[PDB]
Image 1 (tube, helix red, strand yellow):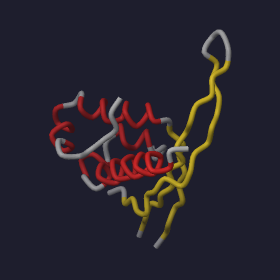
Image 2: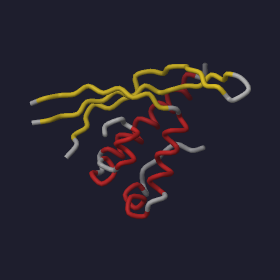
Image 3: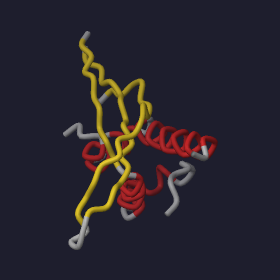
Length: 117
């Protein structure tokens, strides 16, 4: 029932967190996408750290009913432009493949990651 289109990573934001003893920088990937209704379109942006992509896969894998669907979906594993580009490409295709499976795209896990619900 959720219709997601045109999902891509458009850039990054380098932010900061407190470790408890000081501040540390970290990287968010900016993911933009649209949702369709029937003829309305909503624009969406969510910023997620690499670790958040990895946690998403883990949440799905923790659940047998969902894990089955993503057996063959290549996901993340726990400047050098070629590597940055390969990472952006990997993460993008990961999300797109997840969204293309109704049972996964509509899961609470993907919805939360994408800030849809």
